[PDB]
Image (cartoon, rainbow over all chains, first blue to last red; front, side, top):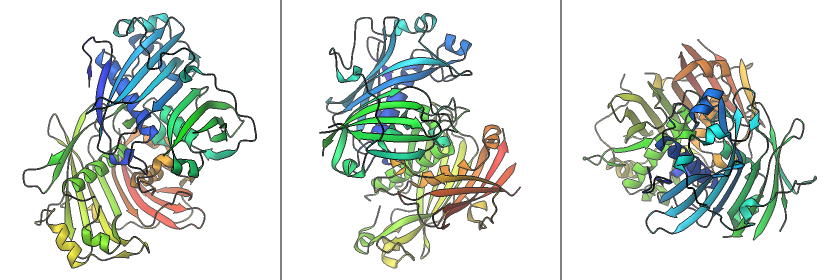
Amino acid sequence: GSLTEDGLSYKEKFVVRSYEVGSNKTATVETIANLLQEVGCNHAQSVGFSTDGFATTTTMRKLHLIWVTARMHIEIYKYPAWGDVVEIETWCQSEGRIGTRRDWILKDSVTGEVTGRATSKWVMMNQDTRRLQKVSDDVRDEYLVFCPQEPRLAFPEENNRSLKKIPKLEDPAQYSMIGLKPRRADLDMNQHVNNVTYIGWVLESIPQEIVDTHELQVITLDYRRECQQDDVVDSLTTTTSDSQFLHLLRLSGDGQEINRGTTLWRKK
Amino acid sequence: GSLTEDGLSYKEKFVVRSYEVGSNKTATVETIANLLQEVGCNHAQSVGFSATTTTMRKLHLIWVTARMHIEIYKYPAWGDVVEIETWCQSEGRIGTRRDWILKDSVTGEVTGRATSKWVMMNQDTRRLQKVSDDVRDEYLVFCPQEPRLAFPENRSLKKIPKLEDPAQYSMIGLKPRRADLDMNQHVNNVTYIGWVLESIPQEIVDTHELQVITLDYRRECQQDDVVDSLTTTTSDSQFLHLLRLSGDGQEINRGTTLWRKK
């Protein structure tokens, strides 16, 4: 991968692997989200944040802070096939002093066709206390020069789906998958549950019939609180409709919300 | 990746990804196993497979893994390039074998090796059988016919005993999610590696590196099955492992691992 000509975004090509695809031999959305992470990380490295930390800045490393996803929104028009090459462009932008966004555009590497778009919002956590905080001025100042100054949005429209408020699912749920637990492969290098595991857990309570007949077009996921390695999660889904669903992940042990989201599916 | 000049082995380079590494920022053994299957798959495709010989398809036969054995000297770091060379060999009527050698791209030093044994299964009945002459003779043209052993000495062929109840350690009630399924909706062979390792104490994983894993595969975990992972220390630290389906206690894997203090 490499920085683009203006130095303010990063592009990388990925060849879709055999184990990264589902039953129609195209990348799963979990694969896509993992590639979003990888190209984001490689972006951070390209501008000088070394592999001694998980895309953290030098102030973060000093203060024992790590990055935490607050929201992920992914829209896929076409999933790349096994052995195909997808090119992903990514950039970071601050929303004043209030928000920190990373955006992505996915393209067919050969034809240049846009095949998907994504965006994300970020906060930080103290790695020791696990307490969340907003990105600080001292942190942002370490990468602001590497970011576009005029607005650059994967989803530019006012009131677009990416910014929509997600309601809380009300019991009873229509569908559930109970007792999901992380294994070691689900952990990132910081020993926190990786952000893509929550996407998988949300999708686990989608009925097989939908998965067999439909493709996921949109996922919007808020991240309220982390699942720790010894926690157990229930995934709850209700139809709100294309087919659309409302999602809630919560801890088995007390019912504490860890995520809420929505998904939009299109018949194959 | 590409075939080598003689057409009898295949090489591919991988850049180790952020989500592929553990707490020491080096590739996990499940990452290694994933890269092994990927380079395997690319090799098979490069020699014209889809993987079944025309004769296998006619007789509704598939290859299934009987054993995976992995030995790692050094796990590649985040962002490092690992080069993997793989080849296959016929083991006459018994089955076939796929071998791998892992190298540091930069130094050319061998950082690991692996070997897997494959047996023929009827896709309908799920019963194992021997390799027929026709299947053998079709396979051979893709393989070095002189033996080429990643493990020439060995631990890779050793018989593994069945763990006796009670187990020292356990992780109970493991279940696959969708990401664990392959394109045919069977559980991916690397998932079973993860499940074996889950019953190793966290204190061992935090302070030791896995040097060797040997894993026999007996029968599969289906999508709706539930697995218990059992471990007992047999010793460096060495462990004996058993995966069984908890609904009936049916064995699906047995294995051993060897760990060295960091």
